[PDB]
Length: 236
Length: 236
Length: 7
Length: 7
Ligand SMILES: [Ca+2]
Ligand SMILES: [Ca+2]
Ligand SMILES: [Cl-]
Ligand SMILES: [Cl-]
Ligand SMILES: [Cl-]
Ligand SMILES: [Cl-]
Ligand code: NA
Ligand code: NA
Ligand code: NA
Ligand code: NA
Ligand code: NA
Ligand code: NA
Image 1: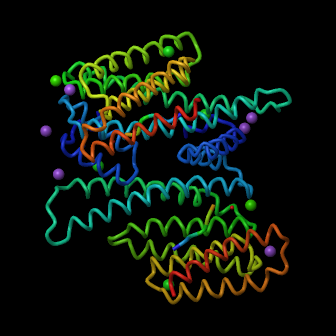
Image 2: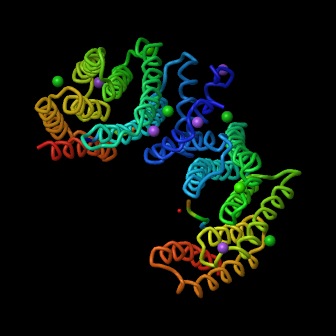
Image 3: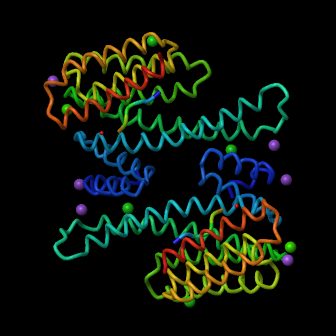
């Protein structure tokens, strides 16, 4: 509650400064503070929340992958025993990553999702819930791996159901949701055919709706469509 | 003292893992822990110490410069009053930066410098002392600005005196010391002519000693000489 | 694979 | 200006 004494508007202002300074841990703490003021977030504020924690967890995920690769190489045949240090430090990074994911999921559960009535906010937060369960799933190995995966799947599915009912196929949130659910299928759920089908249907349905858009909206939608195409090119 | 229960060798091992994972705050904490074991550092360990804190403070310096530029633009004519937030957050980053600098200077004073008898270690640590007083000077404005600058100058000068007596002109530590003292003159001490003279004499004296070097040492020395040339090109 | 950017 | 790299 270290941000409890700062005004909501000052927290948002400082989150934007932290972004300019590439101080994403600060940015996340400011936006957590803003969320804990208890008011719903605007579109811009939701983006700030997402940018901050995307960059924090992004650094942790990249570090975890470096360390996991070293750990796995240490457990091949002919590898010298180097002691517990690699495992220990990988566990340290993994625990910090899980703590960030838990923090985000806690904000969504208390009480961003329950107060989100509009499709754009509700889908945004449910996508975020899927994303941060997906990051937990990337590092999970024990008894709860399956339940973490199902938690991600359930959040993404509720978001998809709403987005398909309430949003046009070119909406960037809908597009980024489908992109990420497709990555979930490919990388987490061992369902590459589901991933490919989802990416292709999403891309084709957005293509057929581009004619309705302004030039600026067209640029926003085609940016995410190109990521879908990039993945299909990687996967096929 | 959170590293007090970990073996020195494990701290060094984990510092090297953190470097591979680009986790420089972790790396700095591991190397601080290793220093606090009380034994002198090897050449490789000194480099690890330097890499860790260079990258930590490097991120803070870059953020401070972004925020200071915003702060200065907020104080021009025709600028809207946005409240205390820019100043506050710049101060926050500045205080964290000063705390890192103080931590390094404290390690050097307790007791790296006093135990360093060889020229290569003593010059390395005195250069570091100059460097971290220089970083403090970059953000200093009040009554102690002049004493901070003189502290940097004094450390660099003692390092120069030893390096000139005890090291060849191509030694990479000697070269990087002179490079940094030249930047001190140009950017901190308002002495651009001293900066230029130092860079040119350093470069010319190393050039005349390259013929004594192996190919690998030649590569190490010419790398730093090119930075001296780059600065001279910027400054003349 | 690429996942979604922040807007 | 450039300052010294870490080796
Ligand atoms: Ca509502
Ligand atoms: Ca000694
Ligand atoms: Cl550890
Ligand atoms: Cl699936
Ligand atoms: Cl602040
Ligand atoms: Cl001077
Ligand atoms: Na208020
Ligand atoms: Na070991
Ligand atoms: Na709608
Ligand atoms: Na020991
Ligand atoms: Na304000
Ligand atoms: Na010597």
